[PDB]
Image (cartoon, rainbow, N blue to C red):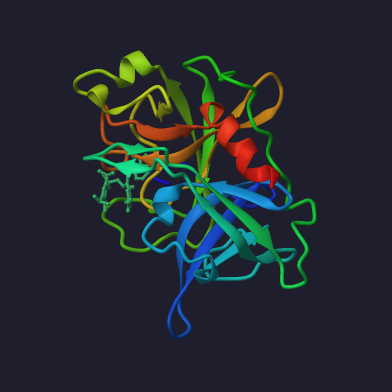
């Protein structure tokens, strides 16, 4: 997250941190995620497409730090990795960038709700926040594009939702951005999500209820003028989300 402020998981209880195991012992960070149900975490397919093995992944809940433990944190295995069948990646745009991770501890149990581990609500069919509304994004992504390391402490920021008309502009993203995507950016282009925040939540207060409006998907650079962060419009994937979570 470029700019913004540092925070704790107590403020982002639904945040999931996803790591990938490696041949040997190293465990690098992959992407963020959001707990939508005790046994389900939603993220971005682009984060896993190259390594479809569910065994190489580790999901953390109630974790505020990148390389260290947090009291009350929970470690999970990926019981099932569901990638969207129609995912594709063009020059900049990443289509159907959504994924589901059924998690399970070593005991075979799911996420036990606590003060540091809560599930965030999904939106109603096509019911999204009106454009110009403030929403938050969380992650362990880069603080500057020049950085090659992720910040140890969890970061967050507020961005404003941008209409499909403004984002579809020539100097913005042209026709690359579709109706299945949302644009959000700082009106001053000072704060934005960046490499590493992918798969993380874009939460909006919809009708007095915290909702998972989008998933950090793509964007040209980080916090560049007229280059908003593009998010997967969670409200257009409800059917897909429901059919794959049932059984
Ligand atoms: C993969 C490669 C072609 C590549 C593509 C791109 C974009 C043009 C899509 C970049 S960027 O800074 O402009 N963008 C990176 C980082 C990013 C992510 C999410 C949101 C923002 C935002 N502005 N708010 C920025 C990115 O989109 N992604 C998502 C795509 N991704 C993948 O690996 C997809 C794998 N199929 C890399 C990180 C990079 C950086 C290393 C310079 C590398």
Q: State the image coordinates of residue 168 (x, y, percent, origin top left).
A: 29, 19
Q: State the image coordinates of residue 70 (x, y, percent, origin top left).
A: 67, 66
Q: Residue at x 39, y 37 (%)?
A: 191
Foreground pick, 150 / 83 = 83
Measured along the vertical axis of the image, is residue 233 above or below residue 9?
Answer: above
Foreground pick, 48 / 24 = 48
Q: Is residue 104 left or right of residue 66?
A: right
Foreground pick, 91 / 222 = 91
Q: Which residue is farthest front?
A: 247
Measured along the vertical axis of the image, is residue 14 above or below residue 60?
Answer: above
Count of numbered tags = 0
Q: State the image coordinates of residue 216 (x, y, percent, origin top left).
A: 45, 41
Q: Residue at x 76, y 67 (%)?
A: 108
Q: Is residue 89 left or right of residue 201?
A: left
Q: State the image coordinates of residue 158 (x, y, percent, origin top left).
A: 50, 33
The image quadrant that residue 28 belongs to is: bottom left
Q: Is residue 166 left or right of residue 239?
A: left
Measured along the vertical axis of the image, is residue 10 above or below residue 178?
Answer: below
Q: Residue at x 51, y 39 (%)?
A: 137
Q: Residue at x 25, y 39 (%)?
A: 92
Measured along the vertical axis of the image, is residue 160 above or below residue 34?
Answer: above
């Amino acid at each position: 997250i470029i700019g913004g402020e540092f925070t704790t998981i107590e403020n982002q209880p639904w945040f999931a941190a996803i790591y990938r195991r490696h041949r040997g012992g190293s465990v690098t960070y992959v992407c963020g995620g959001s707990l939508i149900s005790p046994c389900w975490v939603i993220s971005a397919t682009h984060c896993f497409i190259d390594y479809p093995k569910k065994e190489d992944y580790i999901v953390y809940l109630g974790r505020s730090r990148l390389n260290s433990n947090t009291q009350g944190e929970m470690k999970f295995e990926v019981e099932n990795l569901i990638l969207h069948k129609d995912y594709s990646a063009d020059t900049l745009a990443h289509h159907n960038d959504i994924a589901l991770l059924k998690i399970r501890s070593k005991e075979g149990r799911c996420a036990q709700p606590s003060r540091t581990i809560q599930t965030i609500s999904l939106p109603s069919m096509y019911n999204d926040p009106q454009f110009g509304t403030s929403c938050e994004i969380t992650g362990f992504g880069k603080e500057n594009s020049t950085d090659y390391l992720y910040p140890e402490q969890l970061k967050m920021t507020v961005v404003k939702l941008i209409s499909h008309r403004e984002c579809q502009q020539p100097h913005y993203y042209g026709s690359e951005v579709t109706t299945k995507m949302l644009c959000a950016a700082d009106p001053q282009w000072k704060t934005d999500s960046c490499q590493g925040d992918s798969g993380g939540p874009l939460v909006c207060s919809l009708q007095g209820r915290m909702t998972l409006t989008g998933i950090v998907s793509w964007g040209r650079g980080c916090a560049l003028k007229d280059k908003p962060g593009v998010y997967t419009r969670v409200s257009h994937f409800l059917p897909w989300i429901r059919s794959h979570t049932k059984e």
